[PDB]
Amino acid sequence: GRLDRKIHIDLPNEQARLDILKIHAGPITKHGEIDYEAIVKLSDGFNGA
Amino acid sequence: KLLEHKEIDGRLKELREQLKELTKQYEKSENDLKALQSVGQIVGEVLKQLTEEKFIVKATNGPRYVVGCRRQLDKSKLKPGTRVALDMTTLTIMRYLPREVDPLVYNMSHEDPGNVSYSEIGGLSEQIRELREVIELPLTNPELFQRVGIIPPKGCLLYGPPGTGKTLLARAVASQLDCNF
Amino acid sequence: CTKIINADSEDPKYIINVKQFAKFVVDLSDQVAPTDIEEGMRVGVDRN
Amino acid sequence: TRLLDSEIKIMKSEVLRVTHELQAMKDKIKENSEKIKVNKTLPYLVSNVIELLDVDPKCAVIKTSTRQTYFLPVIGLVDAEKLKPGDLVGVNKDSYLILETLPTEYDSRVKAMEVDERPTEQYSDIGGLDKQIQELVEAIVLPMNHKEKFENLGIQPP
Ligand SMILES: Nc1ncnc2c1ncn2[C@@H]1O[C@H](COP(=O)(O)OP(=O)(O)OP(=O)(O)O)[C@@H](O)[C@H]1O
Ligand SMILES: [Mg+2]
Image (cartoon, rainbow over all chains, first blue to last red; front, side, top):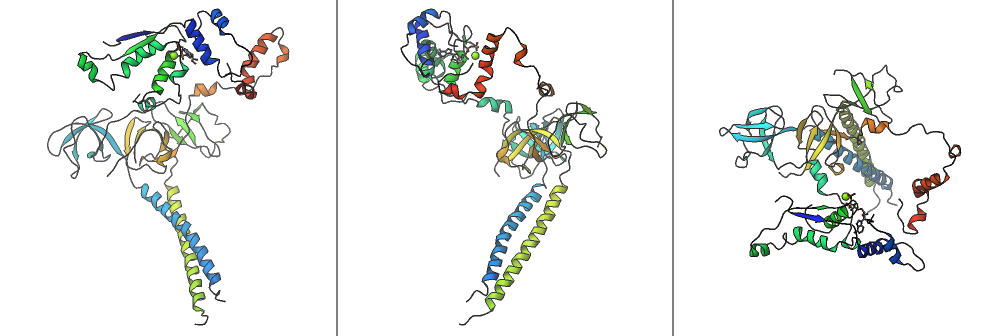
């Protein structure tokens, strides 16, 4: 009746982590070949920050 | 040939050019002297009227006064609770004013140079829909809930570990919606 | 006794704050030099 | 007809009259400026601007530092284009009109914590902290003097 809805924003998943990495690593002037799978596997319990 | 007046004509033209600025200066001086012949008025709130010519009004501070009103002013707009301006030497009703807006609320009303959209936030495509289900659809198409026979909720809160994207989502919602905020 | 809060250049135009009354814009007197008028310290002030 | 001296005389009289009028207007302007400067008694009253309300047949609503609310049918000697809700203004003590605009004020404690006398210690008198010094200098000093090395790559500083 005052705060009707409680919304939870938990830590990102592997797909969510890959999405955030693709969002933030885009604009940088990259070179060569990049492999996001190892980065996703290593980063556990991380945040967008 | 006929330039006997040409030198004097040029002198007159230069004098007129100077007189243009001299008249702008005279006008500026006139506005300056005219502006400095007015005084301010105290501000208060009306409570009720005793008779045709007597009201009782309360200033912003404590004291309450029994005062008169101007003759030409309309008396049909002076309902209790409105804001009025009174003379500082006789305390007579002179003018009614609209409701106040605080400078703090004015600053709070609009402060957002950010322009973040939904493309810069990812990984929580379900909670964003859950939130938008509350503040977007009912405010535009309100007959659906009336047809079903319920009332949409009012508020909600977001919680979780630090740095998961709460204030960012709030900024995106505020920056991508056409309504008072 | 009052407290100066700040100042401005090329003219004293000192901003004076008091505990109960309002704050004003003021200047010095004739016998006081502008050297020892550093901000944030208590000063004497007329009544009028 | 032939040439006539009447035009020269008329033009000379017009030039002289216009010059005399300009001189008289300048004298009147000087007198009015003297009167305006007479009304600028130095003790003002600092106050805060609440509203620049618009009315029809600009009017200000202000809050003096002595806890009084005032309504001004006219602004005064300051244009209304450079006023915002919350500005700090000096107001005439009796007529209660804006006379000038003042800079934003800050707390004395906040102002007193800014450095004045720079220290004299150099990097040469610290031993055994090379990695820490390098890691600190590349995150504070570097993004100030070499910003062009950052946006050329597309990376935000720490
Ligand atoms: N899903 C996401 N996609 C992209 N960036 C994200 C996401 N979640 C968080 N971020 C990053 O988080 C940063 C700041 O997060 P934010 O201010 O929303 O913190 P928070 O979750 O509200 O935490 P807190 O307020 O408790 O400190 C943003 O600059 C952004 O880069
Ligand atoms: Mg936050």
